[PDB]
Amino acid sequence: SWQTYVDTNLVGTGAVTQAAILGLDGNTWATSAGFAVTPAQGQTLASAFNNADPIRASGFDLAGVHYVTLRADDRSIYGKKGSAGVITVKTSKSILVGVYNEKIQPGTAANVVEKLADYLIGQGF
Image (tube, rainbow, N blue to C red; front, side, top):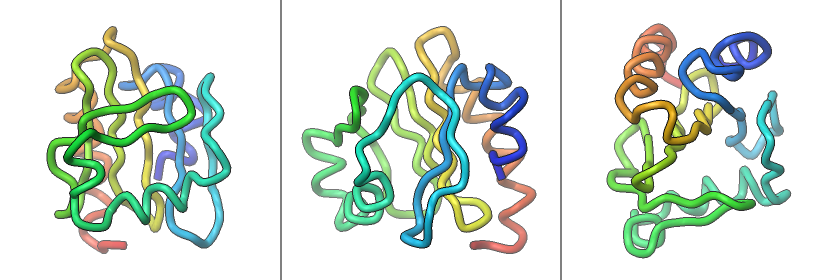
């Protein structure tokens, strides 16, 4: 879903000053930011979603960013750390990753990512 919205606003700063689309062990789709995630991107998200134990306690880490992760098991997963935030939710067989800094509020980005998804939720991937 963020594919076409990745090369325009959604990523430039249409809610997040950075965003990437990874997940699903089938392949990648499209990313756009200033951080290279290790090759274990789709392998760290599918495994991180085991029992909300590793992501809940201690939190998880990536190339150079990490969060505490509050809830992660229902369907959406927008984690935060107190300054920046990474909205990781599923849509069209892909987990968008709204990577933004403190400039964007954890609510202004969760509101736009909630409506866009609302469109792809009717189907459910």
